[PDB]
Length: 194
Ligand SMILES: Cc1[nH]c(C(=O)N[C@@H]2CCN(c3ncc(C(=O)O)s3)C[C@@H]2F)c(Cl)c1Cl
Ligand SMILES: [Mg+2]
Ligand SMILES: [Mg+2]
Image: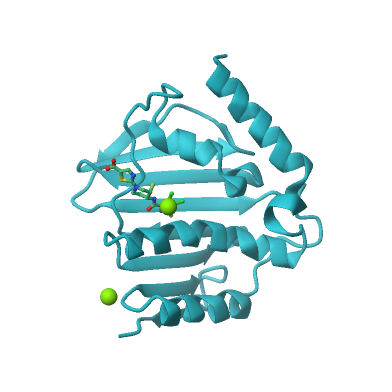
């Protein structure tokens, strides 16, 4: 329990104690804000010149999956924490703290790295699970029903409106929204402004 790891746990406690101060509310608006917090990272990575595709999927039981083709969150052991950079970044994430479960897959160094968390707490050390010829970041998360008491069900039209807006505002980025909650009836909208 180093000073860094203690700071992490205190940070998770603070976010879960007063979630509304971080994401505005714990209502339906707050639930959808989780998606924008993650997608904003991918947008910045695109604007920095390293990504051009973002995919948002509403998966079974209202998991959200966000994928980009950026550089991938770094996995090198950093100086401050002595932990992989990706773990440090995600253990300070408000979305992670307010999710009952969160998973990351980083495609980087021709390797796929995986870590999972519950309420921000890593469930195991970052591990290599496969290989890849792509780079990018995949985040899957399930909003915490203890925090989001009114609803944990996403509204497709709400996500659609803002995703369309984000593509219009950030030209060149292909942004795709897909609803896979009903496997028999799957909806997809893909936006790409020139
Ligand atoms: C979905 C998603 N995507 C990103 C993301 O793309 N983050 C970038 C990845 C590249 N970064 C690098 N930092 C240092 C790098 C290096 O090579 O040293 S690459 C900056 C952000 F972390 C994040 Cl964070 C999330 Cl969450
Ligand atoms: Mg960033
Ligand atoms: Mg493009």
